[PDB]
Image (cartoon, rainbow, N blue to C red; front, side, top):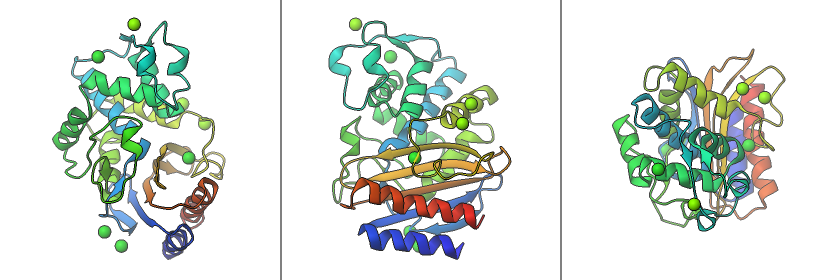
Length: 263
Ligand SMILES: [Cl-]
Ligand SMILES: [Cl-]
Ligand SMILES: [Cl-]
Ligand SMILES: [Cl-]
Ligand SMILES: [Mg+2]
Ligand SMILES: [Mg+2]
Ligand SMILES: [Mg+2]
């Protein structure tokens, strides 16, 4: 909607950075709205949904078990690891790690999951296999969050990741049980959801994953809609801003508020 595009432009002006935006119809994949849809942005922590997709593909294939216990050590622990820092001595199962990575934004959990699949290159190969030609993961947390100028590492485009999320959450890439488990993780309540959840109306469905990195990187991918059922995918990315985190959050949240208002 033009009203949403105005809010995307206002965000670029206020934040002093590029903003990328896409909305897709969930059922058809038709592009409803877009702004800088094929420009590159850091994935930031939005990659964690793609990662758990890859894990679930391996579960479907009999190559991984959700109940497999992963044991790890103190120097696997990186910053922003609220769940994994509670399990150094007992380990965590693969399903516990995906829940932690997606719902609690746990960096160590995502790194351990990356190990389970064989690393960033294997995630990139899985993406290529399912038809995503743009998205790339090169590094693990927190390195992938650096957001360096002119660096193509750990980037996607809004259009590419929107299409990939649609492939994972709908149709036949994952089994129904896997599809439902990924949605469950993404729908689970989080500690704070400033970008879309905070103002989302009661009774709306939302399955989302946000990310924040260095150098102004911020992103969210989501499936959402009224009446407890998703009907659109929205992706919003920015990088480069040196505005405060609160200002960055507020400008992105206004884009979401407009999407909902003019739905
Ligand atoms: Cl454009
Ligand atoms: Cl573009
Ligand atoms: Cl492993
Ligand atoms: Cl959020
Ligand atoms: Mg050990
Ligand atoms: Mg649930
Ligand atoms: Mg809820």
